[PDB]
Amino acid sequence: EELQTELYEIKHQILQTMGVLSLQGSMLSVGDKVFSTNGQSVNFDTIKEMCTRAGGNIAVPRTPEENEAIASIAKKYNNYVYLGMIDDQTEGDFHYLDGASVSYTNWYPGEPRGQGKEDCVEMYTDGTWNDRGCLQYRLAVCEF
Amino acid sequence: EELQTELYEIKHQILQTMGVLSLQGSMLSVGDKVFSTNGQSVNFDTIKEMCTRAGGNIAVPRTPEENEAIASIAKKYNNYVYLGMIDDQTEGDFHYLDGASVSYTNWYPGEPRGQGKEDCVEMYTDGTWNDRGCLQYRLAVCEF
Amino acid sequence: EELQTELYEIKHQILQTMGVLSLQGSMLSVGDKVFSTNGQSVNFDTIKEMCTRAGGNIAVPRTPEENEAIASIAKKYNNYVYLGMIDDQTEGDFHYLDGASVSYTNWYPGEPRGQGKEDCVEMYTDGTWNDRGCLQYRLAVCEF
Ligand SMILES: O[C@H]1[C@H](O)[C@@H](O)[C@H](O)[C@@H](O)[C@H]1O
Ligand SMILES: O[C@H]1[C@H](O)[C@@H](O)[C@H](O)[C@@H](O)[C@H]1O
Ligand SMILES: O[C@H]1[C@H](O)[C@@H](O)[C@H](O)[C@@H](O)[C@H]1O
Ligand SMILES: [Ca+2]
Ligand SMILES: [Ca+2]
Ligand SMILES: [Ca+2]
Ligand SMILES: [Ca+2]
Ligand SMILES: [Ca+2]
Ligand SMILES: [Ca+2]
Image (cartoon, rainbow over all chains, first blue to last red; front, side, top):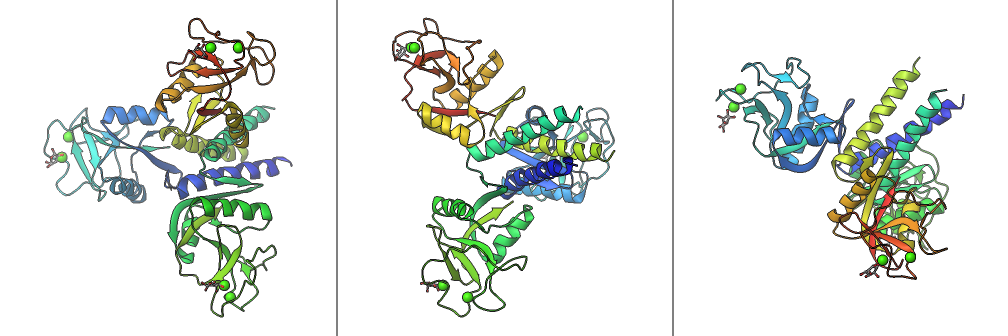
């Protein structure tokens, strides 16, 4: 019976810290997912490690709203973003990093194409996607 | 019995994140209320939306200590602050945004006056209040 | 039975806020300890008050890993760091601020020495320690 008062305070305090981080542009909240960036431009492998170290994962949009959030960060920092998906196994079918087949997509018209040996996916500042090599310097955006 | 250990860790972690935000000037804590700003100067309506989007509300002091906190942010950013109170209905009696009548006040001597058509309230950098129109650019301060 | 869903969401949200603060360099997490700095260089007494106001304490490393974390902040800001330990009572034996005798140490070779009247401890940017007077301007690093 004293849990409710205890749980309320906990939930309230969490709302406060999330409110502050949100108000100050430190992160974006979309449903249960929080997106954030450290502002750095590094390669795919480095991004993965940065996100993992923080306890999260390299961002990947699974809905238009999530896609738009990531896109907004992309245009805010004026940089393309590496997404949490690859097709290193067989070309054409992309997978999330857990192995599951990609469902929601937002390819720029004609994409994926050009290759060949393009295993990664980048997001343009308008939110559309392009398959690309994994060694370029791109904005690190993480999901928690 | 494993809740206590679980609740302790949760409370501890919350204290940590609040500690960090507090240490770095990201927010101010006064009792159960957290104040924060994104540093922007915008009109009354815009401030309201900014705070609401972050899950909070435009700040309003109900005690001298809360008033002093907001005042400190005001002088830190060298800007006046719109407060969460209006008197758009009948002139003279101000109300919080939920409708309740304003209790604690800190009017600069002679205020409210001048109008007429001044429905909003701004805080000077010394913490005293002035009634003012709602279209000026003022520091956005939110409470959570 | 609805606590699990409630506790999960709480734990998840906490992970999110800690993830964001961590990703952005706002703090360092080592075991159960969080380290953070406001970037300011002030004396020992001022640091203590700054940390206490934020709900934490002036940092003190009790393991090599904690020592390395603090050291990284030290070299990041290119400043030496006052640690949460003193020997104001009798010279030679240092104590944590709760009174307990210091266990883990990492003195630079030859230290402590020179004095005499050196009651505080500073960390060099390589992580080694030096006993020093308590009135110098040093990076404020707090633990939560
Ligand atoms: O499909 C695109 C396109 O061909 C680009 O112009 C090229 O720079 C990239 O290699 C590729 O990802
Ligand atoms: O009462 C004040 C005062 O008259 C000010 O000098 C004026 O600039 C504002 O209109 C008003 O809020
Ligand atoms: O032991 C050291 C050493 O002697 C330094 O060169 C001196 O600047 C300090 O007084 C002391 O902490
Ligand atoms: Ca390909
Ligand atoms: Ca392509
Ligand atoms: Ca009026
Ligand atoms: Ca007036
Ligand atoms: Ca000494
Ligand atoms: Ca010495």
